[PDB]
Image (cartoon, coloured by chain):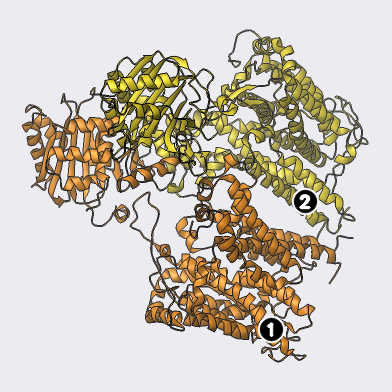
Chain colours: A orange, B yellow
Amino acid sequence: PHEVFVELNELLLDKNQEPQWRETARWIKFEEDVEEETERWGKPHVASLSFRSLLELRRTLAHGAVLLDLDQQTLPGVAHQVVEQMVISDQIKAEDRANVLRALLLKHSHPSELKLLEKIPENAEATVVLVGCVEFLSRPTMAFVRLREAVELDAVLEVPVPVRFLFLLLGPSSANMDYHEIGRSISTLMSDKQFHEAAYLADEREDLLTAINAFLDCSVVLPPSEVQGEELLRSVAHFQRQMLKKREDPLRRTGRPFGGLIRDVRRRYPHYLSDFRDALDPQCLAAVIFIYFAALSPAITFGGLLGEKTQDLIGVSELIMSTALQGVVFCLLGAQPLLVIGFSGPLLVFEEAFFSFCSSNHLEYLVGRVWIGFWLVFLALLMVALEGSFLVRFVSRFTQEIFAFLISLIFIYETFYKLVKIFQEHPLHGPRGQPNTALLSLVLMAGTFFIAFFLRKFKNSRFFPGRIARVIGDFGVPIAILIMVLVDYSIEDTYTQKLSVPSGFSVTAPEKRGWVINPLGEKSPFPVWMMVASLLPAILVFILIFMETQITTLIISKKERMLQKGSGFHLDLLLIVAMGGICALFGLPWLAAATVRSVTHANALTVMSKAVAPGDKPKIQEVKEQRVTGLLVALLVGLSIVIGDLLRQIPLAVLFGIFLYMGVTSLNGIQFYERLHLLLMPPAAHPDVTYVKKVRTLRMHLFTALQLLCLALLWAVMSTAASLAFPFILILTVPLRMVVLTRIFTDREMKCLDANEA
Amino acid sequence: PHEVFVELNELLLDKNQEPQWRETARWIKFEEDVEEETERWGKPHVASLSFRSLLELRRTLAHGAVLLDLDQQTLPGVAHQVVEQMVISDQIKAEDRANVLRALLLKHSHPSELKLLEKIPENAEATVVLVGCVEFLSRPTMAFVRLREAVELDAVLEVPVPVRFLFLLLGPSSANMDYHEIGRSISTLMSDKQFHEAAYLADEREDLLTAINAFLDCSVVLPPSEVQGEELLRSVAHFQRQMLKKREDPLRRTGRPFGGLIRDVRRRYPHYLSDFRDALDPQCLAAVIFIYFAALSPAITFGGLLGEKTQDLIGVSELIMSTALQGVVFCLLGAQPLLVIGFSGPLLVFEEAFFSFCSSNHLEYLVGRVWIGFWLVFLALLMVALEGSFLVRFVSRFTQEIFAFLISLIFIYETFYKLVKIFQEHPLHGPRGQPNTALLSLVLMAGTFFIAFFLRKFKNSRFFPGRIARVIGDFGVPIAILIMVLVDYSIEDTYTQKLSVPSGFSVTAPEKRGWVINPLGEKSPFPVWMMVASLLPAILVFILIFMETQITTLIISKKERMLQKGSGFHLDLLLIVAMGGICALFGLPWLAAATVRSVTHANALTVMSKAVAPGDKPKIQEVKEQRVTGLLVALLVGLSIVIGDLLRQIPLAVLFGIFLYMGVTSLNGIQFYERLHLLLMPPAAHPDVTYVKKVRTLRMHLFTALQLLCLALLWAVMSTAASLAFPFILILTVPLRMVVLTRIFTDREMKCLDANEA
């Protein structure tokens, strides 16, 4: 089976009023049409035919000329043999054979070479369709030629490809046939996957006719009624699938303890040296630059906020080093260095939720986190030993979207509650009570949000090339902070709460904390009941780390990602938590492998294949798969503590704008949020999605109501004094979905509403 | 020719495990398919067929049964006659005739009546397609029945329509034919405009077969290659037009002086009493409510700004009365009461531009406008007398889009220059010098912009029904002002510049001005050279009124608007200017018939026809065409001066936010702005628009550069001391387009780049 690039060049008059063949269309995949007015190739489109043209093609092909395995290699000699064969079958009178021969030898023309060769598959044989209105003849005349050898004909094609099938059609007008449409019909057949397969094996004129019928019976005949909108033709794609259908792992559990750890070590580690060679490509150097701002910006927005929530015990300087200390050690030893380890959003809403519990019960907060670390290590060892990392299968779209919607509700609430706090501390009247502090904070808070919100749309708009914005992922955030910091920097005599960052490798609050947190009680003795009961917070933390890291590994290890090298589930979970349990001893926060950063890292290294035919979705040729982009990003984040002066000038109102921005944008893409929109829209206006078409409106609104009810239970718990339990309530939905929603919704509805990939 | 509603109900098993015909699709126009999973009718779509099904239909129809002019009216009797005719032609054995008869008489079923009757044309005759898999037969069997009389059959259709054509098909499986697809093929043929026309006149089985060929030869045969995106199938609509194509005034000038005035008086005035009767419909009462906020909100945003630009000589109170004084008199006497007369944007940028000239040359500003009024009256009489209102043909998309883009540049600039003025008068430090005044003004200015900007998107989003938002046009502006006024109202001890509106029918600045401006000089004598040279500003004003009113009358008088009553060009131009020349004597501003308000008024009264088949674009059945909605809106605006306390609490920073909002949104829809976007995007990403497809990229960028160069000439003039001349420079583009761009661009390119309607 050979791929075919079929070119239709028609006999037309040039600007010099001379007859010459001009390329009118070409078929690599689908069809591209020359616009005579502008001499520009049109956008690729489905080669729609006219049934009258196909009927005329079938009529002329019967009693037509046939040149099979023509042992000729020169266009003039081939043309002379074609004319002889045509006059054998009485198609052309011997008087006009000279004129037909002269018409065959005319100079071909094209609108304009290396670029187009890339799109066509390398091992392809082109088909030339010579169709034109000839005046000296009185009857239409056709000749299908199959060359014995793939001979690159003499300057006949726009792109030099060995010509295999030569198609000739020369007939006068007034025959009620459009030769331009007959040329498109025969060219479309030759580009068809199965029609040319019958052309290679064709042995008689009847066989080629039978090949047409095998094409028509697989076709779609539209009616002559016109089309008013694109939604009318949306079902044509779905119907065309029905017609053709009628014609036609790391999570595996082994009994060996630490078995998943051993397999993942034996998979990626053999490619350790290869992990450093693949980094020499210049695309990796662009990944370091554009991901460094994707891993540093959330390191200060969460680092700054932890400075307020935890009274500067854990601030930016600790989160900067914790991101760098773990980011380097993970890349040097992890099985998936494409993961960007960082302080996830859900972990932030736990530290704020755990600080209140330690503040209420008169427990040292930092020492209370040391003992969570000692129990995070034990649970991580226990789970990896028993290979219990396959439970991420049960965490499905019902639980993920409830969580990702609850967090985005917290981010929106926490800024607006911070904003209300500012106005109550700095009321509008003619440090506390500072004029212009409340409003400038609102301007900065709403300045970075709308700058970053609109630049995200500009990223996704038609202005930015897809090949570029894939590499540079979410650059609105770094520039929004830079712009509004300078806006606040220019202002003088007005106080805005600045980021609390001390210069040098020092604690954010040196007077209150030391580098090594004493596990036995820093200032006051630590109660012996809490060091044993810290397992309960540790399980709740471990759920937030296990869910965030293992889901992320699932997202980037899919076959669509084209990750050739081994991806490790067990080895990453152990490192992310065993470092998190040891980084807690030094007061540094524990981290998870965030999904948004990791995909931004994975996308930046995806190399889209150049050999894509026009009109086809780009396919990921490969991914760089190196340990250096993750390593350098980790080191550069750690070196951000060198600029402690620049970070100290970032207003805290600027970060809350980004904090609100990340809350709002994370809603996009969540089916829970999308199905909340449908709760307001009328049933007629619901979009044609899988969960909408195959599920009736009433059942869909019941499913969304249950998710919304399961989200109000989480919010009620979070506002009470037992806010630590929201990880446990969250994974009560997994028993709920697998047991309660199983008997309410049929398997058909759950397969549509809870889809692993969609 | 009868419209046909063709229903395909197939023989299928019910939830009771009993055989009964179930409606699977219906064809009023295009096709709607029953989704078996949810029992919901799918969205209308083109009835795409499979060529195998059409071939099987043609095969079975040959040697098939034919019942033409069957003189029967009962479904059991018709079925028995059909069975007799089928067994005559050996299609069904006499042994199985009882089973076929039993299968014909089965109870039909449908998913669910008055609503669907509206969509179908009233005088229509339905076609029933009975297709099902019958097991007791060994061969497929078909019977096409054309009833002699249009008999509403016994509960056979979902919607009771007199059945004319009855189509029967009963055949076993294993015949390599999908009866559901054969049923869709025959149903699609019957719904075709020309196929059933041959069915009514059909006289033999051969004739019906020939009718199929007349259908296929007008069809579009898609290839079996799948479709990846909707842009692939976008060309299918364009190609389908080619296939079918191959098969197939008030501006008039008369020699009589004031001739246009007489015709327009003799056209609309006879319907004067009808203009008041048509207003009793409840839709008119909704127009008054929703347009009152569309005519009042720009009356204060321009009224407030004129308070600053003209030092409160002409403010809100004068613009409110001028809008009401002219709005009432125009509706009582104008030939097109659908016009909403109001202070256009271009007139605002002249009063600001004319005030500077009067301030620089030591001329009384208000007296200087009285003499422009006396010369506006004379020019209006002169133009209407000579019927020179046909010059609006020459003001084309080249001049309109240059103007509408220049103004939107002024609106954006004027707010940002006001905002800079506030900060320099109220600097940020720990009336003048007021703290919190500069930032709160920015918050209010950016508050109303983003509230109104996002609510405009919510208006156009899928959430808001199209039938509603057409009635309620641009309601984001009234609610944005209301929300941010309350936000500023709650604030205390902070000063924001409030609207300057005195309560009662009083001048905005009583100490400086009187109600009647003395034409001979109010305080100081008016120079006798300026009262004669005021013709020069009068011509420049008259261009801004003529261009804005006559273009608006063109926009709403198009045939697509379905304005049955006479629309007047000459009578409106005379009234709008002759009142404007007389309203200037009292210090009130002159007004034009704004396009945006008028279309918002015209749309609110358009009654969309209920008798629209599914999938068709709604057609405007009629427009109310009354003089009362315009009258009541005018009176309600005048009564807004009663609430002088409420208007006095609107901050001037709130209005500048709306002022900026109207500048930004007016850019949308302008091809000049759209072609500026293409100047940045690569040629591959250019949208498939008429001026893009038929004009090469280099020539299009030359045309846009010329427009951008012609916009920089206007801005340079406007920033100089002769800012009054921008009306004259603007209509220098009409000679430029008709003379200079004629020789640069071919008529093919100008027909695409400058399209009157697109």
Q: Is residue B561 left or right of residue A489?
A: left
Relative to B210, is B240 above or below? below
| Residue type at tag 1 | Ala
Mark 1 nearby-residue class (10 Å; few <14, some 14–19, many ≥20): few
The residue tagged with tag 1: helix, strand or loop? helix
Mark carried by residue A679 = none
Going 53% across and 80% down the picture, which residue do you hit? A383
Q: Mark number for residue B444?
A: 2
* Residue B214, position as x, y percentages in the image: 32, 23
Image mark for residue A533: 1
The N terminus of chain B: image quadrant: top left
- Judged from this view, the residue extending furthest toward the right is B511
How far, Cα to Cα, is label 1 from label 2? 53 Å
Q: Quadrant of residue A278?
A: bottom left
Q: Please state which amino acid type lies under the numbered disc 2.
A: Leu
Mark 1 chain: A
